[PDB]
Image (tube, rainbow, N blue to C red; front, side, top):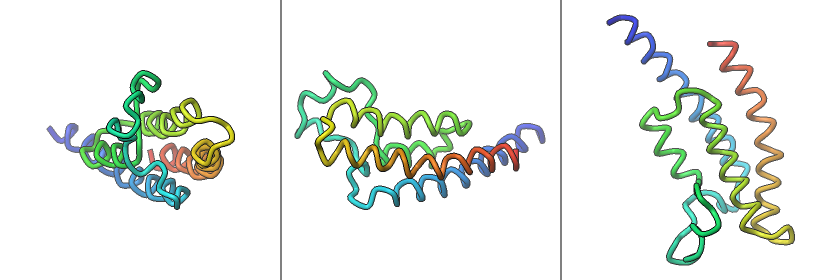
Length: 121
């Protein structure tokens, strides 16, 4: 149906805008602390602590399969990256501090993305 097409075009356009959001969030992580999954070979206990691991590579796979239906879904995954790191790592660590900075800087970006998603539809 043409209706099914039109819905697909909207998903595609949301995917475009989410890719640009994702690029801009990832630039706020020049250290690449959140670029890849935590390795279960190097933190064998990770899954006893963290139930839903997340990282920018995993978000990017989902994005390219058009797996985010709305901005809320995408934000949930971004928040997992931050929130998981702030639980596993202590306050005095380069990891926790990197998550706080990514959260603060990412807030700015997400605030305008929400306006753009509402604005364009």
